[PDB]
Image (cartoon, coloured by chain):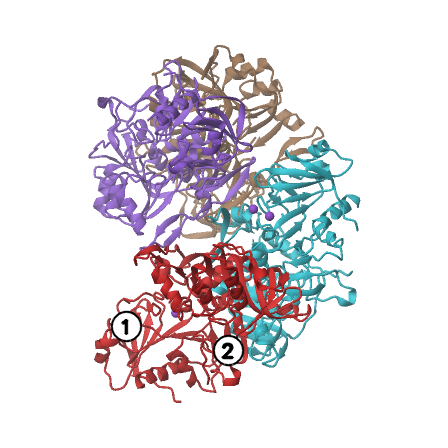
Chain colours: A red, B cyan, C purple, D brown
Amino acid sequence: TKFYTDAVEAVKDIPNGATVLVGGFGLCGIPENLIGALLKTGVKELTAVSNNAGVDNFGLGLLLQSKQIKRMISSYVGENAEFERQYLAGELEVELTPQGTLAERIRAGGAGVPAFYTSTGYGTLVQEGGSPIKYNKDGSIAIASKPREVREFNGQHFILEEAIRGDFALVKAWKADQAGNVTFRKSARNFNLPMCKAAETTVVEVEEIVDIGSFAPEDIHIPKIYVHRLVKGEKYEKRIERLSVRDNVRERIIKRAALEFEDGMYANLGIGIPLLASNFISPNMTVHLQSENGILGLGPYPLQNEVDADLINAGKETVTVLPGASYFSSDESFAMIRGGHVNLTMLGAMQVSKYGDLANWMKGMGGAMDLVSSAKTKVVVTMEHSAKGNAHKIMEKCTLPLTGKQCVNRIITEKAVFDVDRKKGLTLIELWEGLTVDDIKKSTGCDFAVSPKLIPMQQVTT
Amino acid sequence: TKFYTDAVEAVKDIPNGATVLVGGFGLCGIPENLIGALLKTGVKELTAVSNNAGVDNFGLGLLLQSKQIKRMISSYVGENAEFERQYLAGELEVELTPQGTLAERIRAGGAGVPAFYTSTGYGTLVQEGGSPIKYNKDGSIAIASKPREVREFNGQHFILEEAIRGDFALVKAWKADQAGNVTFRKSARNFNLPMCKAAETTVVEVEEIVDIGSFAPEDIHIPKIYVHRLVKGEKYEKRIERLSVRDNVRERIIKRAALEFEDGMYANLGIGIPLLASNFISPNMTVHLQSENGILGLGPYPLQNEVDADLINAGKETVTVLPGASYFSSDESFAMIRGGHVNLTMLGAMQVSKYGDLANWMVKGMGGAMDLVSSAKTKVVVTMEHSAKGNAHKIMEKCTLPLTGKQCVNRIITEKAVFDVDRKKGLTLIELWEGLTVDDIKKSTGCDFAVSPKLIPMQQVTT
Amino acid sequence: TKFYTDAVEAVKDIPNGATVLVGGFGLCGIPENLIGALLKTGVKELTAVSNNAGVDNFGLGLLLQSKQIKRMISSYVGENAEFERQYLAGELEVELTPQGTLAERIRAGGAGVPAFYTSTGYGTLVQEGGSPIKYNKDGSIAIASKPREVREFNGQHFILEEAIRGDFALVKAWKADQAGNVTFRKSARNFNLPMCKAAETTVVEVEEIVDIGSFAPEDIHIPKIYVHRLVKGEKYEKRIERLSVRDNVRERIIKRAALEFEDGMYANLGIGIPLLASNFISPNMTVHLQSENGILGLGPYPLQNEVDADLINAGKETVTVLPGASYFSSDESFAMIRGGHVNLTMLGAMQVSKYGDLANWMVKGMGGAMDLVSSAKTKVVVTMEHSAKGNAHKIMEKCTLPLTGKQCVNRIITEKAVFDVDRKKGLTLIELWEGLTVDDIKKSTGCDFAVSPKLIPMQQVTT
Amino acid sequence: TKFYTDAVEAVKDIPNGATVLVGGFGLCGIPENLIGALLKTGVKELTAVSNNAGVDNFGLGLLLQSKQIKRMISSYVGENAEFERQYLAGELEVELTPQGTLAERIRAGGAGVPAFYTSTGYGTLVQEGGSPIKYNKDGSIAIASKPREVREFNGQHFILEEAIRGDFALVKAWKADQAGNVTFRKSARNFNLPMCKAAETTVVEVEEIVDIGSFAPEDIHIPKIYVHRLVKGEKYEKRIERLSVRDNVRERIIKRAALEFEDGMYANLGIGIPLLASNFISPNMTVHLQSENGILGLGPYPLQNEVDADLINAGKETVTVLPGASYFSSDESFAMIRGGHVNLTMLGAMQVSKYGDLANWMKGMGGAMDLVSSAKTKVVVTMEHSAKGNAHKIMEKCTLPLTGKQCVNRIITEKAVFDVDRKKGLTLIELWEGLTVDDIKKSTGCDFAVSPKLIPMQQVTT
Ligand SMILES: [K+]
Ligand SMILES: [K+]
Ligand SMILES: [K+]
Ligand SMILES: [K+]
Ligand SMILES: [K+]
Ligand SMILES: [K+]
């Protein structure tokens, strides 16, 4: 590892056009000083591989403001108006790739794996191609995404994704010892860890340099072999994107969603109703919440003194963890998710089809496509029954872009609870008292079986 | 995580015929108590996915001795005569898979990836198929390995390997906290870590159970989500397979090999000459030695009282590590190796071809040799005696022995010469042992070679 | 042999899902009446082993049109849009197998040989696996071909291919005597002959039934032992797929290709330039042209009134044969080819590599191209325009198109140069089109090449 | 094709040590003139690939007398005392290879196939190796055969055999036209046909040269491309090795064996009882007899005027064929046999095991190992029940060299008829009247089931 006292020195040789991997999930674990250094070098036309686009004036957004990025390869680019403007104007190219796929393609890039298969994105536009990566000033499409090759293994369909390697990686880390060994703090690890292994030259900025021997050998997150250039970041603003401190239809969904929790369950909860539902878990029940940016054991929002820029949830809110929590990188998080280790994945949806196709993302798909990619994880959708104008949200076929095909196992609305089966379709198993099966018929766009043991819709006791 | 006080209770439901992942590299990090529990349950016909076969009376060898294994899926199975015996007799099935491929297939299996590509094994018997996985009693081949599918990416060839998942995994770990979070000690991590994610039911035995909060959250090697059953092992023998404590032709190779080292270099040294050469590294030079069983920063053999069963090198010798060393799992180790992060890989060879094909492994298995030379980014340097007994060529047009890799050697160091090897142009004699002539080399080499315009007498490290 | 007066009676017991071998090369020697009988029985989901797919409305194309075929195992399936349509739509499965391998696998299937080795397909997608045999409606790959196992014999690589056997074979023959002995006419023999031995129940339709004793015993092509069911075909359309009756860059290649011919030579000429070159053979020179569909002694295209549906060349063109010609079956033809008995094989190429890899076939299938260059004993001469549109290199370090063969080309003839090709040393420019310079060739060739010390202006046949 | 007027001219360049393929089955279709020419050139140390060793003073035996052969690769070398003497004395090397395997290895050699699998020889010394190929003068072994690799396919075991290619082939043919196209007459085709394709230089001698155009193109047995050198043989002796012109225990076996015949059956009959049994086939029944030297449709022994050196059966007897007979080469004959196209193969045996192993060959195995190699062909053994001294011939395990393993389906003796099953063993289905099941018990060396429908042993009506 080569140590630098000046960040510009550490990155001055990045060529125009370089593919640069930039760590960070939201504003968590971003290499703010290395990004500050690129503003000074003025290198341009970069293809930035960055999970997110920071915010308008921070993180990757600073490089978008200065127009130093030709293309971004990211999974979620919301919360950044300059980004949106450039994209629509045809000034910026954008390849949206599922978050877990982005993590794994980066990991493959550092592991000598040119390509691998993942179900994430199967049946969606990731597979189908056709998304505008780049527009012409006239508003037409200049570059459309390529469809992905898909192959069946063990009766399931998987898309072939290729490794992502960078010319450079700009990595934010916590500490580096004098040998160049590096560790990451809390959830700031995310993509920084795998990105450190996937570029020809990795540049890491750390908050502190410690003596060789400060780390237990077993606990070095990134061995020095991956750290080519190391600089102690000069300034850390610790920006927090969203400071989060500790109707009846919605309340009803929350209260029935709260009943999906089981003792010992591992769950991943999308923001909104699913997350609110966790507030009703019995202190008697032990439920472990997984966060896809690399956390297992999420706790409630922090009391003001617990607020930590390094600890946010997938919705980018400041959060806390419970005793016995663990942190891990983004590739490891999605290995955990894709491998079906989470028992329950509960999320909101705009539409769900008869056989469980889900439309809930189209800013980018973030980790939603990965979260529903495994048949081993029970996917529970919580959403209001019908859309504005009473248009069906549950129907034969989604009309909105799919997040996944035949991946929903249960739908919870304020009116009903449907179990969903990829081959047989819907089964009404709970019914809000006061409504009748025919009321459901009228608000649902496809047929459904009625369970012989249909009960009034339950509501958690709390 | 469910805690058990009895190991048999933790594994009694394993079915006959189950595929069981068993952690451990050699005797390092083996789940000796869970294995002991399987001897009691008597479950049989297991397909054991285990990097190695332990030794005759320990680790997986115990289950082979009791005949509870139908098939082993391993990368290296030497040091076991009952294994050898059962294999040749047609009583045991064996699929040899490159060590790094095994680690990655297991990882894939826990990560939802059904298959991936790797250059490891391309152009070898792994790709080619035809190795006997199983013999019949009369010596006929009952099952031959399947060839692997090939695909080209970015101008190179890779083979398609599929995930490995087990019904159960028997994992050895260091400590578990009360929530089921687990950590591994030193090099005992190896395959235990990835195997914990790749089975329907993971059973972990640990040396000690500690309070929730004993681990820093960032430093939990295996989050509790992957630990289904946990037991504190009742007995730990701390078996050490090889207790390693601190001619001229060979010495010459060693001394020229020592000159391949450069300050700041990351190197992986095979046992024998390569490793011996590291003893001549200048205390002025900083060289980081990587061990494929998951270590970066290997040090010299320990004094006797420093020996640690949890710390061994790839040759299964007890070792030490230097300040700033790190440990990591087998899949990570081979990601590091396959990704080309090691600058120099120096190993022994039986044969090397004109364009750099290497034969240096063949039934004991290829271990990590095929992975070690799988990347074009790592410089591969072979150190071997020039010619075989009877002066048969070892360096020639084509290897006649099973390949470890195709066009992967960049340099050959023998007691007579040093050849740089290029996949397109072939051999270039760049150093010549003084007293020998270019014609002497011609006579001991089985293919043509260019003679560098800057050919020098063969160098020898100063030490 | 059991005689039938009704074709439907002869095939009514074929089960849905049966594997059925169907004779014929193009529309030559196809069992049109048995196929017509299958349209009436309606049997479905057949795995049809048929060299070709007939044409849209004839031969196997009729069964594709009625959707009675689940999978085709063929070597060449061009000239059929319903086939193409069903394949891409995921309605039809297709395993492309080299023509000669198909013939030999079928023969093996009737000879009790479960598997054999052939160099045909080594280093290509046949060995490598991964071709889509079947797509799903959304375009995903439902079934990918399996790679083939490799083995080395006498220093060369071969792949292991397995026998093909059918439940039934639908065979077209010329005459059967009353005992069930059968003969084939001209080139209509092709696959019909070997397919008669490789199915549990063989059904043969013939044009005429003659008295026992009409055949000389030595001249029965298929002994009655292989003929289980026999029917005199009710109707024979004598369909002819291609009625063939007797620039300067291209002309230059042709005229230099014509100089590859030698008196007494056995040659196999691919359609296009190679075949055109044969028109310049001196009536003084005797050259015997072999056709892989089973002919030795091809002659010029016939006058219109000499056209015979039973006599076509490999490009499916109607032809004639010269005095002393012979006909033989497809397995025999490829034994002849694979055995290296043809002295010169001249074909077109899309790309040729420095060491002689050839890309000249790729989904229509590789036909006999992979077999044609499979032998080191046959000189393989490629005739192609030097560079592709946009001047992209066609001759280069490595082909970027699917290989037909590895290191199998011995010479390249373009409108600018003639290169001898050596598998170990590469290219040697031996002739140069006058007016061009060695540097001009450098600019249009994607790899280095030696310049012969005896380089001459490119020759042109006198005619 | 190059035509020669002098045979010596056609073969003078054969090197000492050359591997030479010599056509012929017994004395049928031997290249007598080319062999005469080798006597004059004196080339030595040849490895002669020849199905048989001719007889003492003819065919290959002439080359053995002159000591010009170092090694023979043959399937049957009986009827030649000089051969036997040299072999035992250690002067001649001998590799016995099953006839059908020899044919197929030669064919593979001309077809570009380096190796193939065949069940022929599985479970026998062909697989096991250990046969002396060469003795030392002291009577010990100098060279022992190598075991063959065996691999399972579709649940069956097959041995890997490698191609045989020659430096030269000496081929006897009937006619050649002026272009070099060649045809073979009757059963003289045998190995000459495949040998013409498997050597670097093929030399063919023919009885007559005819005009181009004499052969129908479809009926050229060997296209000119395979005929490198052609000579019209100067002399043809038409030697006939065995001139064959048209007790009660043995008679009983014959009469019960005659009942194995069925209308429309294809059968291959070994010499002795099986062949004698065919004399009792009803003129009402149509049975087609296959001869492994390349004939289908064998008829009775010839009346003196029908005697033809070109037409002999597998026992090398002069024979005739019936209307509608066909001739074919040795590789094609064994493809027919190995592929299981013959319905019934009836042969004599020295021993048969409980599960159907057969010992009936140890001169060489000839085609016996191939004849029983297919599970599709019913193998019926006809033999006297017990050996001299009443030793068991039917027992648990044969003690004599195996011809095949689990390949016998029925055993016919003068006392009993046993069906044989590879998994269940023996089932006594017929019993010679006057004998009891216990009498069979006493004469049989293993247990056997007694059919519930056991009948007195049948005897053909004729
Ligand atoms: K699911
Ligand atoms: K390398
Ligand atoms: K390589
Ligand atoms: K060639
Ligand atoms: K080749
Ligand atoms: K049988």
Residue type, numbered disc 1: Ile
Dividing the picture into quadrants, the one containing residue A110 is: bottom right
Among all residues in the image, which is located at the extreme bottom? Answer: A462
Query: Residue D120, image x and y in percent?
Result: 50, 39
Q: Pointer 2 indicates a residue of which chain?
A: A
Count the marks: 2
Against A62, residue D63 (above or below) is above
Can residue B228 be seen here? The reply is no
Tag 2 secondary structure: strand
Mark 1, Cα crowd under 10 Å, few <14 / some 14-19 / many 20+, is many
The residue identified by callout 2 is A297
The front one of B45 and A294 is A294
The residue identified by callout 1 is A394
Query: Residue D274, image x and y in percent?
Result: 44, 34
Against C273, residue C124 (above or below) is below
Q: Which residue is at a point 26% across and 68% down the rendered structure image? A: A396
Q: Left of A168 or right of it: where is B267?
A: right
Q: Does the residue at mark 1 contact the one at mark 2 (Cβ under 8 Å)?
A: no
Tag 1 secondary structure: strand
Q: Earlier in the sequence, mark 1 or mark 2?
A: 2
